[PDB]
Amino acid sequence: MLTGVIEGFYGRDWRRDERATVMDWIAAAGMNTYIYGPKDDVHVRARWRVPYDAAGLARLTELRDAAAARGMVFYVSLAPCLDVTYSDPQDRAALLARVDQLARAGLRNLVLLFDDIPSVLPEADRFDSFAEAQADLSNMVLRHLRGAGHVVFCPTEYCGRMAGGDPRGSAYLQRLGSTLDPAIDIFWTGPEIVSEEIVAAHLAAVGEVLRRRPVIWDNFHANDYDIRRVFAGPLGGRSRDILPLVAGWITNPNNEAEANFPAIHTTGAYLADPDYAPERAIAAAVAAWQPRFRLAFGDGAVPSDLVALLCDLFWQPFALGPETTRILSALRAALTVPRPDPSDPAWRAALEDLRDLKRRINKLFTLMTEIENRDLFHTFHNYLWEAQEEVGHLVAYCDWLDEAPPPGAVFPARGFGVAVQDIL
Ligand SMILES: CC(=O)N[C@H]1C(=O)O[C@H](CO)[C@@H](O)[C@@H]1O
Ligand SMILES: [Cl-]
Image 1: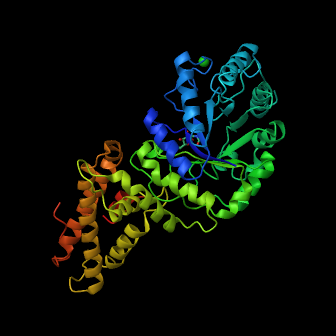
Image 2: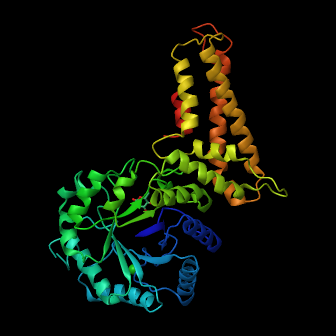
Image 3: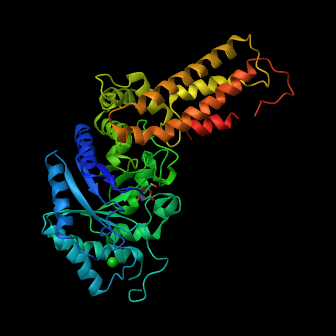
């Protein structure tokens, strides 16, 4: 089974040290695949007919080798879907020269992406469909490798919603399933681009129409679409019972390399462990992550409980972490009335936990500014700044209610920020 990371998100490309770091993490998580396909690389997509430079190939072979050194396989992406005439011999040879330049460089693991297409088939073509054309084009690529290499296909309709709800209801998928060579794997992101859950019944349906088990392309931890947010919590919403229904697991992670330690650590635990539990898994990721938080000029590091807090604040796309969730729910239960009673123990307890949360966020903020690893600092600073401001606002508001102000009086002047603003 193919497992690992795709560098396939909308952001900056990683440096060579960053890719090397990510590769260590993937291998340590017991995963086996790294897929190269950054938007930085003009050859991947924007100008796909243009073969790599001598130096560009060199860079890729280097990555292949850094991955092989780690017990991982390395794939190269090609996205000839925007301006493709699927029947044109000039385009076909150009695709084939791309494939051949790589194949002969000894880079035979490929992804072919068809995610962004023209609304109608190009005149010099209208096969019966986009599906048949892409399928034919992809089979060509397969037949060119002569059974020595591997191809994964990213389809145009890659989640339930884009397939109309039930994937068995899509014609593109119907046709893709029957025309695409069975040696070629197909990506799927679940019922949505960013799926809150991916359930067994859903993937049974997908398997039927594609006539094969899909390779998961999981966007659970991606943050390109919302640069206001980052996801440092554990992989959630996918039961272990869906794994017999898949051909693979590729994570599309956060834009910033340093952000991805927990996403990779917990995904790998999900893949390896029958008893995977998100809260237990994030505890192990924190314990293994903490050494990256060494303080500058010092032997000490950010303490474990604060690293744990970081994950808790910036948890999942559809959930704040359990610790901050319960602290805010207890405060909500106490704000059931407009004027909390300062003497009430329930309000007293909620408030003190809120105030403690602020102290802890403030320590974490300050400590992060002092860490040796500046990239890790840069990765989190702004998210932490917002967290620290709106817990500040929440405490000032509740500190105000704790003075028994007369009613009528007015206060003088998914994730953490929004949860807080929802309470205001
Ligand atoms: C197959 C797929 O998911 N493609 C894009 C997408 O639509 O969603 C992700 C998260 O926004 C992006 O990083 C992907 O490049
Ligand atoms: Cl081009």
